[PDB]
Each structure stands twice: as structure tokens, then as C-alpha cells.
Amino acid sequence: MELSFGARAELPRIHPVASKLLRLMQKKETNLCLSADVSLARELLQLADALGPSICMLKTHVDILNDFTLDVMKELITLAKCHEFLIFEDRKFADIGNTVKKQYEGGIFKIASWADLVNAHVVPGSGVVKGLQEVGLPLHRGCLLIAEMSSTGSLATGDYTRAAVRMAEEHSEFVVGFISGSRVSMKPEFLHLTPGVQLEAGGDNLGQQYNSPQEVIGKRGSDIIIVGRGIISAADRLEAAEMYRKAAWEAYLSRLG
Amino acid sequence: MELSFGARAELPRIHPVASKLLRLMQKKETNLCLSADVSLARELLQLADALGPSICMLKTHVDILNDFTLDVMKELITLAKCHEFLIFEDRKFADIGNTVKKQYEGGIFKIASWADLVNAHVVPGSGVVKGLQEVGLPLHRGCLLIAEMSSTGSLATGDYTRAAVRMAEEHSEFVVGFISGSRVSMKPEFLHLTPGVQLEAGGDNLGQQYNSPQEVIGKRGSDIIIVGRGIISAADRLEAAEMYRKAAWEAYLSRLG
Ligand SMILES: O=c1ccn([C@@H]2O[C@H](COP(=O)(O)O)[C@@H](O)[C@H]2S)c(=O)[nH]1
Ligand SMILES: O=c1ccn([C@@H]2O[C@H](COP(=O)(O)O)[C@@H](O)[C@H]2S)c(=O)[nH]1
């Protein structure tokens, strides 16, 4: 009784951004999000173009790009359109509502102008969502709430995770899903994206902990895997991206029946 | 048995950044931090120069500055040195450790190059501190941990606040204090900075809640008030800044004895 991505795209209460994402996931047979954690625009754009066909989403940290310009994001949008993926700026908004409005819309980055999706921490209360929504809703954008984290010592557990789910439910015109390690909402309209994913077990020296695609998608019920170093540090990023795509997509299919 | 700012500056376990801050607070008789939430470099630099003598710290959001350049931060450093205040970039780092390293050091903003202090959320676990420390410690910088928030619905309460205090204790070579609404640590080496401060009662429409200087400093035991709109929206920002300085400084003095 679990709906395919394609069916989820047609759900009555689905956000237009999620519906576009779910349709291209189904069409392209990819539930992989590339975490393009690179410091040079040329590498960001070469990864986006080569791996574009293999991904449903490209997750950015534009505040690490040494040569950021708006023209770089224009070229990135051209590739997102060509290859059909969404752009997700992983900014983790977590300030008071009044402040996040200007961070999302303005400054040098003008995130709301090119980011299909942003994410936000729920620790400040619902004002963080309300502030972002004042910019994002008129621009037809979506937001993800951070309901759990993959890093050691995370405090996003128990009642904190529950607060994030309730917050999402109550703001469904803008909040389209979660960053979590597992399915945290029983409503199929919400997307679940899981970072801290690698084919092999382990972590890093700065608190990151990894789980496999089959575990996160197949057993823990998430929709999309967010993968950075497992792809970016490989020699052949395209075959690495294809390996992760096949793992996550088959895990999804075997969960469907 | 409460030590003056001047004495706290000499405590054996005090961080060099906190000691410099505590000395200038004492010398200038100001425990006021100006939240310079403006979008134009000219207004940021005109506020820093005119209110510099009245402040112990200028808190920035460089990601809302429409015309940010590194030369703007050079001119801001010239004013911080001239007038003797610290610069605090209110970035609220809250990502995995590996990611925050590059956000703090690199990108367009090169925050670590000009920010005496940054702050960080504790929700990801201690990896956020460890990541920032790898850049900040070699540069002799300090970090503040967000132990409580002033916004409605905040989840930074109870065991979350306690986790932030423990995290600070265990990283005292880099963590110099807290963003909180009250004294949360009994160790005088740590600084307590409190936002959500205005002379009059009220809030905003996006979740902000205000308390007075006398309440935050005098009754709740914080060290420094962080004030934005109560100064920036006033016609005469200098007299507004002087009003807040006198409130916070007298409240401190009456707490001493
Ligand atoms: O809870 C989270 C939330 C976000 N991320 C992001 O996902 C990417 C993973 O990068 P990787 O380890 O190289 O695969 C990084 O950009 C970080 S901030 C997490 O990791 N955990
Ligand atoms: O828990 C917090 C942490 C930080 N701040 C920041 O302090 C400033 C207050 O701005 P004001 O309302 O205009 O005085 C803003 O930049 C916000 S992000 C809080 O408010 N609460």
C-alpha cells in the first residue's frame, strides 16, 4: 500500500515542487542527490553536467565556492533544466524569522532566485519557517526541515524530531519534506532525504557517520540519499554516481513490492 | 563575590579573545553589542564609526550585505581597532564539522579572516565546534555556542541547553561563551550575550520576543545585551545606543554590589 514516486506526485495535498521532483525521479529512475561540496565553479559545473542524468537533485553549499557569481548559478540552472534535476542550497537557516528573510532573498547570493529548495533548522521555533515563507512562497519555492542529523552527538532526537514534523505539517504550503535518517512522517506528501550515506561503512574524523543506501532507503524508509565524498572523492565520479543511483533505486523498488 | 569585567579578564583559564573583550568593556564602560542588521556597506560603516565608542562589539550578518566586498571588512576592521570593539559574525554555523571548516575559512566571505567571534548551534553535536576550531584556533579566534534562543517556540531548553554548556566546557580553548537569555554557566571565564533586548516590552511579527536590559543583565545575570532594531530603527542611532549602553552598564554595576 506504498505509493510509487509517480503516484505520490499526483497526491491532492502535494506541493508543486515535490510533484516536479517526484515525477523526474520516476522518469529518470534516480533517487540520488549529489552533494557537490567543491570550491571551484568549474568543477561544480563539470560535475553537474556529467552527473546530471544520474541525479534527481544537486545539493549546493554556495558559501564555499571561491569564485561564486550569479552567472555561475545561471549556468547551473541551464544544466538543471537540461538534465532535469532540482537545485538544493543546503544553507541550514536557523536564525530568527526577521533575519532569515533577508538571508534567503538578498545579500550577494540571492539564494531564493536560483534555489528550488532550501533547508532550515527548527531550533528557533516556527518563526524560521514563517520568515523564509514570506520570500519563498511568492517565488514557488520549497523548504526542507532538519528533523534528524547524521553526525555524532546530534540533539535532533525524540521530542525535537517530533517538533520538526509538527512544524512541517502546519506549514505544508512551503515545507515539502525533511532531512532525516529515516521516515519520520507517515504522510506520503512529504519527502525524506538522508545524508551520511556511503556504500562502505565508516565515517570521518569530524563527526560524520555513514549508512548504506539499502539501509536508509530499504529498511529506514527514506526517499532520497544525499551523497558527497563517496562520489566526489572517487576517481570516476560518473561511475560512482551510477553505483549510488542503482543502489538507492533498487532499494526503493524492493520496498514497493 | 562576583568579579568585575576587569578582574574576569585576568582569570587563569580565560581565552585571549574574551580577555581583550572584557578589558575594553571595563575601559569603555560598555557591555552593549550593536546588531548591525543593514543591507548597505555605507550604513554599516557609518554606524560602526559613530556608535563605535558606545559599543563593546559589532554583530554582523555579512550574508545580507548587498555590496559586500573584503575591502568593506577591511574598513570595518580599521574602525573596530580605532574605536576598540570586537567584530562578531552571527553566522550560526550548524552543519557537520567537515563542511563548517570551509564555510568559516573560505568562500567569498572568508569569515575567519575578519571575525573575532563567530557563533554555532549545538544541534549537530560537538563536530561543529571541532570543525570550526581547526580553522579558528590557529587564527586566535573565539566561538560562542547558542545555548538558548529568544524566539517563540525555541527548542533550546532543558537538556539541550545543558548539552551546549558541557560542549563549551570541553572546548574552552576555542569556545569563549554563549548566546543565551540568562547566565547558563557558573564559570566566570565564559561570556553570556543575550539578544532579544529592547527598552520597551513587545516583539515582532516573526517570533522575536524582547526583554529589557535591566532584566537580562541585572536579574538574569548576562554580561552583554545584543540590540538591533531598538537602535537601528531609531532616528538618532547614537542617542539610542547611548541609552542602551547606560541601561546595560548600570544594570551590571548594580549586580556587582
Ligand atoms: O544531518 C546532516 C545534514 C546535512 N548534511 C550535509 O550532507 C553532506 C554530506 O557530505 P558527505 O559526508 O561528504 O557525503 C554535507 O554537505 C553535510 S553539511 C549531513 O551530512 N548531515
Ligand atoms: O536567539 C537569538 C540569536 C541571535 N539573534 C540575533 O540577534 C539579532 C536581534 O535583532 P533585533 O530583534 O532587531 O534586536 C538578530 O540579528 C538575530 S538573528 C536573536 O535575535 N536571537
Image (spheres, coloured by chain):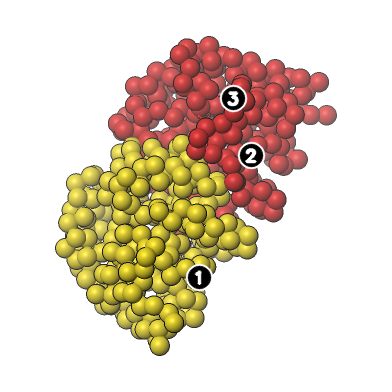
Chain colours: A red, B yellow
Q: Nearer the viewer, residue A102 or B190?
A: B190
Disc 2 or 3, which lies upstream in sequence? 2
Q: Chain of mark 1?
A: B
Give the percent coordinates (x, y) of residue B257. Answer: 40, 88
Give the percent coordinates (x, y) of residue B38. Answer: 31, 57
Q: Which residue does the image show at 48% across and 40% down from the upper left?
A: B97
Residue under pointer 3: A198
Kindly give the residue lying farthest to the right in the view shown: A1
In which quadrant of the rendered image does the N terminus of chain A lie?
A: top right
Q: Is mark 1 within 8 Å of ligand 2?
A: no
Circle 3 sits in a helix, a strand or a loop, which is it? loop
Relative to A151, is B50 on the left or the right? left
**Which quadrant of the structure image shows residue A149?**
top right
User: Hey, what amino acid is under mark 2?
Assistant: Ser
Gap between marks 3 and 1 measured at Cα: 42 Å
**Which quadrant of the structure image shows residue B104?**
top left
Q: Is mark 2 within 8 Å of ligand 1?
A: no
Residue under pointer 1: B186
Q: Chain of mark 2?
A: A
Give the percent coordinates (x, y) of residue A69. Answer: 31, 33
Q: Which residue does the image show at 43% across and 56% down from the upper left?
A: B172
Residue count near mark 1 (Cα–Cα under 10 Å), binned few <14, some 14–19, many ≥20: few
Q: Which residue does the image show at 35% across and 47% down from the upper left?
A: B137
User: Hey, what amino acid is under mark 1?
Assistant: Met
